[PDB]
Length: 105
Length: 105
Image 1 (cartoon, chains in turn green, cyan):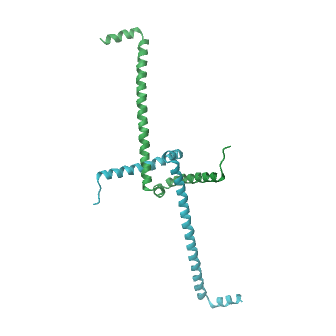
Image 2 (cartoon, rainbow over the protein chains, first blue to last red; image 1 turned 45 degrees about the vertical axis):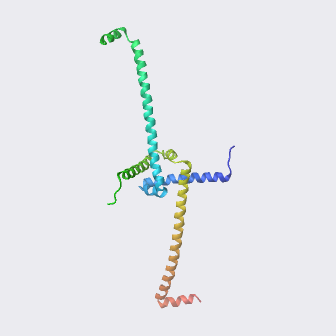
């Protein structure tokens, strides 16, 4: 099978453990109301600003997709209503259709 | 007083709100067991690795300071014990000092 040298396996295992220890360290900082000073210790001012900007970009990407999905579903529902209205008019009883023309003058 | 243009005040207020929204977004992700995929969305693999490495550097800096503080307190306690032992020997009754020399042969 696709294996790897014991050097690369140790580097990947240390990299994994170091990342898990960061996530757990920040989790306990949130539970002790100490996440704000820890983030200032872990991140430079430019890196914190980059993270805030990335949150805005994600919001702008999600809202752009949502409005695009709503526009697609609105046009599809509008077409579905026209086709369903046409079929319902052709399937309607003649008494109803005869009366609908009289209201149209 | 030291004020600032309304442009810079708006940029600083947006920067502040964007950072607060990131901290709150990650806090709710920890409470929903969704912090791991959110961090992968917010951070590239190199940036996550850098954060794990920074946690190890902080541990190595703190342990280096702790062992240096323990070495300083041990040497100070050792000197304090010698000076306190010397004073206690000179303040001891003569009956005790006379007997301590006899045990020394």
